[PDB]
Image (cartoon, rainbow over all chains, first blue to last red; front, side, top):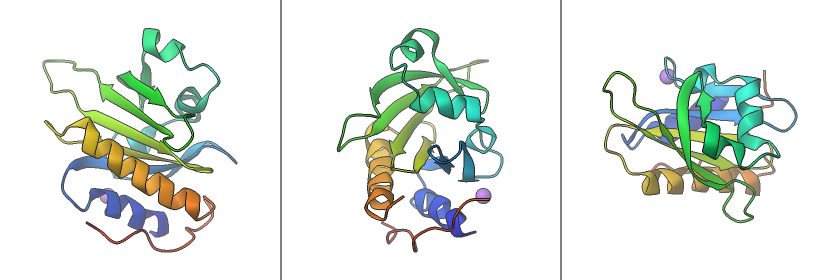
Length: 139
Length: 13
Ligand code: NA
């Protein structure tokens, strides 16, 4: 409800089908997420793969979010002053792909997923801006 | 559950 207001904020402009605030530093778990999305089901294992030391493996093997197979388009998670990743869901059964942006603050990750046709650029700006705001607030 | 947020999120666009 407190962190849910942040999810609501991320969703308010109509471009995202889901969003989430996800702890990674003190412990790895979802703090808040859109009900019924993949982010809600993100596991500690999946968080570890997002934040982990290995920044090359997920370009060969992909990764999952809430067990949904994804590819990594760009990794700047440990580029200071950026701290984002651009991800895209894999298409199964003829379905659209969706762009996902991740912004990393000090304690949490900001996840957003676009609706069909929503470009990664605006999504990245949204995750970055929220992550930056949280970082400047000590989170 | 997690620590509460530091305050409200930024104003919506
Ligand atoms: Na919801």
